[PDB]
Length: 300
Ligand SMILES: [Fe+3]
Ligand SMILES: [Fe+3]
Image (cartoon, rainbow, N blue to C red; front, top):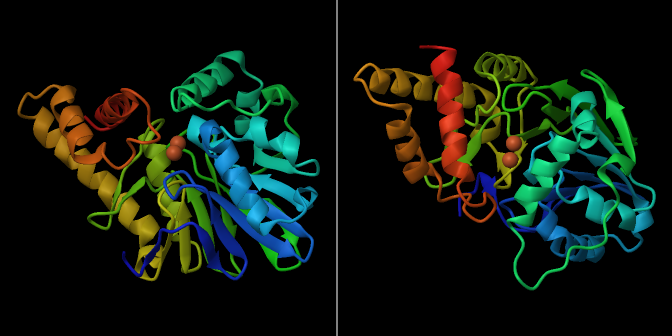
C-alpha cells in the first residue's frame, strides 16, 4: 500500500477511526471521554456494517453527538435515516442547501433509488426515520463547530461538485474533510480525477480558496481513505491542475470533431473501475457525460 494513503478500516490517528469500507467511509472522531462525532454519511446498504464497526469503539451510542455531512449526494447521506434512530443524541450538521434537499420529494426519491440499487439480495434495511424528520441543524459558511475541547472545525463552502457542498477544516490538526470537492483520488496513479457535476467555475474557485488554507497535514476526501504528506499539502493545487488538464483534453478532442461520447467512453473505461462497487448501473458513464457537458459549456 502507499505510506501516504491510509486505506484500512480502523484507527487512523489518536482521535480518528475509519468505519465501514474505505470506498465509502464514515469517520469517527473521539471528542472526549464520553463524546464522539461522525463525518460523512455513506450509503444506506452499509448501515449494519457501519453500526457494527461503531459499536466496537463506542460502548454507549448515546454518546455520539454530531454527524457532519459534506453534501446531499446519495453516497454521502444514505445512512442517515437508518442510523439516526440508533443515535438518540445525535445532531446532523449540514449546509442550508443540503438540509433543503432532505425536504424535497424529488430529491429524496433519487437518493433512495440510487441507494436501493446497491442493496444485496439478503439484506433488509433497518427501520428508517423520515428524511424530513432527521435531527438536523443547518450550518453556515465560515461557522466554527465547537465539537469538543480539542475539536474545533470550520465550515467552508465548496460548491462546484454539487451546489450545496461544504468541507470541514480542523486547523489544530491541519486536517481537511474535503468530500468530493477535489475529485476522486486515483489509487493506481496518485492523481486526482475531477468530479465536476454542477459548475466548473465554482469548482475551480473552491479549490483556489482551499489552497489558501494553512498547509494541510491530513486530507480526507469522500472516498478512498486519508491522504498525508505531500498528497495533503499539495492536494487542492493538484486537483485544480487535473481539472484544467481534463478541460484541455476535452477541447483537443472536440476540435477534432469528436462527440462528447468518445471522451465519456474513454473516461468510463479509464476511471470507472475504482467505484464499481458503490456507483450502480450506468451512473459512472452518465456522470462522465454530465461532467463533460458542464466543461464543454463553460469553456468551449
Ligand atoms: Fe458527490
Ligand atoms: Fe461521492
